[PDB]
Image (tube, helix red, strand yellow):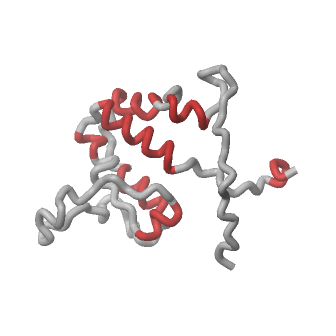
């Protein structure tokens, strides 16, 4: 009946699969055009909250290569007031610069379609073995915010 209602929190995919597709992108050999799709993307404190899974961009230094230059750039001149829009939108906006996105790079994104990791998360339509995560019995079941 919930399906009919249309309300079903948890639609967003888990951070576990997020790493899988991002990892494949690196394997693909994306060009500088899309390397910014991940290298230049820096998640804000709100970005993480709405998009769990942290970021693997890294400042590229143990402490800081050079503070004056400014590690990781989020402010894109193309984006008009990215701060005005929500962080989720902000993410797309930063990578939006990849207009030269190579097909090979794109292939990596679709490469996780039959990945062993994505396989357990995605039943049939590939493995055809009708398999899925066994699930966990250790659930926090916390009250959460109010």
Identity of the residue drawn at 50% across and 58% down: 52
Going by the image, does 35 lie left or right of 94? left
Above or below, 128 relative to 25:
above
Horizontally, residue 7 falls left or right of residue 18, namely right
Location of residue 139 with respect to 31 vertically, above or below: below
Which residue is located at x 33 percent, y 55 percent? 41
Q: Does 89 appear above or below 105?
A: below
Q: In this view, does 13 lie above or below 7?
A: above
Residue at 18% x, 62% y: name it: 62
**Left or right of 72, for residue 128:** right
The image quarter in which residue 129 lies? top right
Give me the residue at 50% from left, 42% from top: 17
Q: For residue 42, what is the image quadrant?
A: bottom left
Give percent across and percent down for residue 74: 31, 63
Q: Position of residue 3 (x, y in %)?
A: 81, 48
Tell me where residue 4 appears, x and y as whole percent.
85, 49
């Amino acid at each position: 009946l919930d399906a009919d209602r249309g309300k079903l929190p948890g639609k967003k995919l888990p951070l576990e699969v997020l790493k899988e597709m991002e990892a494949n992108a690196r394997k693909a050999g994306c060009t500088r055009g899309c390397l910014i799709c991940l290298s230049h993307i820096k998640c804000t404190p709100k970005m993480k909250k709405f998009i769990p899974g942290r970021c693997h961009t890294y400042e590229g230094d143990k402490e800081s290569a050079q503070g004056g230059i400014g590690e990781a750039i989020v402010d894109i001149p193309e984006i008009p007031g990215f701060k005005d829009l929500e962080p989720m939108e902000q993410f797309i906006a930063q990578v939006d610069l990849c207009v030269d996105c190579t097909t090979g790079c794109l292939k990596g994104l679709a490469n996780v379609q039959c990945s062993d990791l994505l396989k357990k998360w995605l039943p049939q339509r590939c493995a055809t073995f009708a398999s899925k995560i066994q699930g966990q019995v250790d659930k926090i079941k916390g009250a959460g915010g109010d």
